[PDB]
Image (spheres, helix red, strand yellow):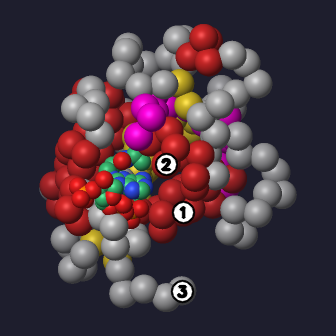
Amino acid sequence: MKGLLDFDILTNDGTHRNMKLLIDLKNIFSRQLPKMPKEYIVKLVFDRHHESMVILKNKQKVIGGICFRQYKPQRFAEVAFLAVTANEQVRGYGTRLMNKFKDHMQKQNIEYLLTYADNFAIGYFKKQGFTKEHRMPQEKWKGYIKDYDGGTLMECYIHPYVDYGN
Ligand SMILES: CC(C)(COP(=O)(O)OP(=O)(O)OC[C@H]1O[C@@H](n2cnc3c(N)ncnc32)[C@H](O)[C@@H]1OP(=O)(O)O)[C@@H](O)C(=O)NCCC(=O)NCCS
């Protein structure tokens, strides 16, 4: 594992240091992301407890990170979103999370991911493995649940025995 970067598992339990960093992630996304609905990332990022992995460009200097939580009886999952802060990206960190996200997506047994990704995260997701397009027409984008108007109903099919990292 090459890279001096530091990652951390945060939660919205309401501790203290976890919040400050968790906050960074929320603004980071909604920030670079065309004024995307803040409450959205906030909802998924602070959707009760939940688990997330951030980045640290100085041991505690948040820069990137992804947050999410899959549903068991639902067999579906939602991602708070991944993304490095503005003029902090283009360094090679974010991708480290997106992949870490997949490894976990399999450790939870949930493969039916979901989000309201826009052309921005769209291509960015389809690039890291995700799939913005589904067997059904895009016209069915409305109905993915949570958040109304903002991006596009994206999904991440976490098929079994897939080459994600393990
Ligand atoms: C997406 C991201 C994790 C990847 O960063 P990266 O691939 O290492 O490098 P980036 O190219 O993103 O670096 C930033 C610049 O590249 C562009 N860029 C942003 N996100 C990008 C991405 N996913 N892929 C390629 N280029 C991207 C931007 O124009 C940005 O311009 P600026 O910094 O001069 O204002 C990170 O750049 C980010 O958080 N961007 C904003 C959030 C976003 O787009 N989220 C959706 C993806 S899930």
Residue found 20% across the figure and 62% down from its top = 87
Secondary structure state at the residue bearing disc 1: helix
For residue 1, the mark is 3
Q: Find the magenta span and give its range.
A: 107-120
Q: Is mark 2 within 8 Å of ligand 1?
A: yes
Quadrant of the picture in which ligand 1 is shown = bottom left
**Residue 22 image position (x, y, % from top left):** 25, 52
Identify which residue is drawn at 28% across, 72% down.
Answer: 56
Residue 11 in sight in this render: no
Within the magenta stretch, is there residue 157? no
Q: Quadrant of residue 84?
A: bottom left
Q: Is residue 24 visible?
A: yes
**Image quadrant where one finds the N terminus:** bottom right
Q: How many marks?
A: 3
108 on left or right of 32: right
Q: Secondary structure at mark 2?
A: helix
Mark 2 or mark 1, whichever is nearer to me: 2
Give the residue at x 44% y 42%: 121
Disc nearest the viewer among 2 and 3: 2
The kind of secondary structure the magenta stretch mainly shows is loop
Residue on which disc 2 sits: 124
**Does the magenta run of residues contain 111?**
yes
